[PDB]
Amino acid sequence: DGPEKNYEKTMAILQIEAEKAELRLKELEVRRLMRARGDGPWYQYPTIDKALIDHSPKTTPDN
Amino acid sequence: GWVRPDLGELSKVTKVKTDRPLPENPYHSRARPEPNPEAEGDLKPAKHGSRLFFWTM
């Protein structure tokens, strides 16, 4: 085929490879922030579910 | 005039018409922490796939 096709195909290849490199670096950064701060969907470690608390009147009033 | 309560009457849960206001924060609770933001939006396929090393899907 003509040189144009290899040229354009190289361009498309390079575009998606560069976007993948950028996405990989951004993923690493998002991972670091999420693991350090715990305000993202990731690294959500379990805490006790508050629906397990019984709020019924106890035998003594101060509880 | 004092009639003696029957079996079970003294164990009833009754109601009292009090004038005292209902306590607002009997537990003296702190403000609860703000929750992590929820997930919104529709799922789109992974951009260029897994992007694991040399894999293209």
Image: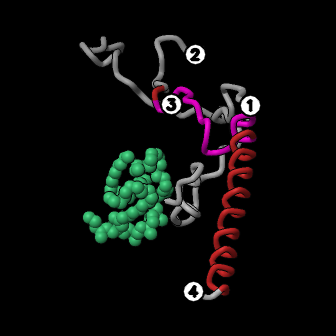
For residue B5, above or below residue A17: above
Check chain identity for marks 1 and 3: say if they share one.
Answer: no
Name the quarter where the N terminus of chain B is drawn: top left
Q: Please report the residue visible at 57 percent of the width from the left and 63 percent of the height from the top.
A: B48
State the residue position of label 3.
A49
Please, what secondary structure does the residue beneath circle 3 have?
loop
Q: Residue B5: horizontal and vertical position, in percent?
A: 30, 14
Provide the chain ID for the residue under circle 2. A
Dot 2 or dot 3: first in sequence order is 3
Dot 3 or dot 4: first in sequence order is 4
Provide the chain ID for the residue under circle 1. B
Q: Residues within 10 Å of mark 4 (few under 14, many from 20)?
A: few
Check chain identity for marks 2 and 3: say if they share one.
Answer: yes
State the residue position of label 4.
A1
State the residue position of label 1.
B30
In the image, A32: left or right of B38? right
